[PDB]
Image: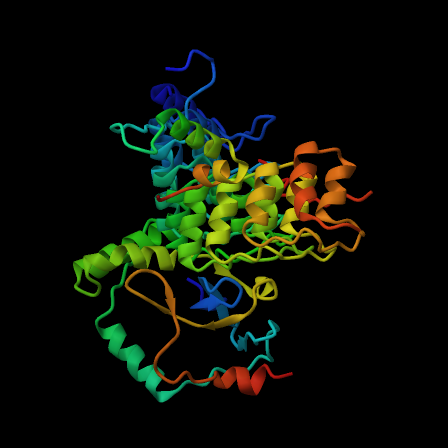
Length: 293
Length: 50
Length: 152
C-alpha cells in the first residue's frame, strides 16, 4: 500500500498489464490486500477492472474472496463487472454467497449481479448459500429473482444441498418461498432421500412436516428408508417408519430396506427393521456437487 | 449433578406431596423407562411442543 | 467524426423463461440496414428501417424533455448508468427512490443471440417497485419485423 511509490513508478512507465505467475495485475494485488488507496490510484490511470489470467479471476473476484468491501465498493462503479466468470464459471456473487458476505452481495446485486448465474456444473449462488447454511444470504438472493427450483447438471436443487448438510433455517426460508418439497434429481432422488442418506434427522422431520413423500422411490426403486438403512442411521429408520415408510417395498436391484441392513451388518438397523419386516451388491448414492474454487 | 463425563440434555423434575397410589421412586422409574424407549427418545429430541 | 457507417444495437429489458429473471436481450441491430432477432435466435433478412407514427411522435416527446449527458468521461456502463440516473434526478425525471432499482435493472446481464438457446426464451417484462419482473398488463403486440422478416 505505498501510494507515493506506486505513483512514482507509474510516472516512469510502469506497466499495470504485467501479471504474476498466478495471473495477478497490480490491481489484483491491491484487491487481495485491501489497499484501497493504491487501487484508487491504479484505476485512475489506465487500469482494466476486468483483467483476468488463465483462471479467469478478476480484481473483483479476489476482492470478494478476501472480503475487501472497500475495494468491492470501489471496483463496481468504475467497471468491475459482476458478470465475470472464473474458470469454473463462478461469478463474484458466487464467492460472496458461499462466504456469507451479505454486504458484499448487496453491492454486487445492486450493480446488476445475477443470482441465477451458473457454474460449469449448473451451480448458482443460491446453491452455494443454501449448501453453506446462510439463511440471510438465501433470503437476499430469493428477493433478487433467484430460482429456488433450479437444478444443477445432476438435478440437485438448493433444497437437495440443504438436505446433504442439514440446515433447518435455510429449508424454512426455501419452503416459505414456494420451493417444491419433492423435487427429483436425474436419478429420482428427493430431498427426503438426501436427508435420510446423510443422517440429518431434524431436516427429515422438517420435510415430513411439509408433506414430503415418505415412500418416494428413485428410478432404481430406492426409498428414503433404504438410504437410512444402507447408511446405518437407526434413528432416521425409526422416524421414517413412524411417518409411514414401508419395510417391504423392494428396489429394482432386488433388495428390501432390511436385506441391505443385513448385508452391511448394521445390527441396530437390522434389529429395528426386523420387527416391522415380514418373512420372505449395489449401493445407492445420491448425486453430489464436486465444484470448488 | 452427574459425576459421569456425559453431557446433560434432558431434565425430569417430578416433585409433589405424599398421595395414595403415588410412589415417587416408581414414578421416576417410569419416567426414566419412557426416556429410555427408542421412539420416545427420538420424539423428545424432535419435540417442538408438549 | 463518423459520417461513413456505424453499428447500432437495440436491447430490450425482458425476462427469460428459464428462471423468470429480468435481463437484457438484443432485439435488432443496424449496419445501414436493420436485422431483427427471431424467437428461434436467428437473425432475419436485412431490410430498410420503416418506422411507426406513434414511435416517432413519442420519441420527439421524450427527446424534447430528455437528459443529454454530452462528453461524459466514463468508460464502463456502470459509470454511465450512475451519471445518467443522477441527472435524471437533478431534472425531475425519476424520483430518488427509483435510483436503486433503475441501477439494478440497467446493469443486469446483457445477453445476446448466442445465449438465447441456453435460456428457455425471451418474453416481455415490466420492472416493479421492487425489482421483480412483471407480465405486461396492456395487450402485447407481436413485432411486425419479427413476423415479416424472421419467420424463415
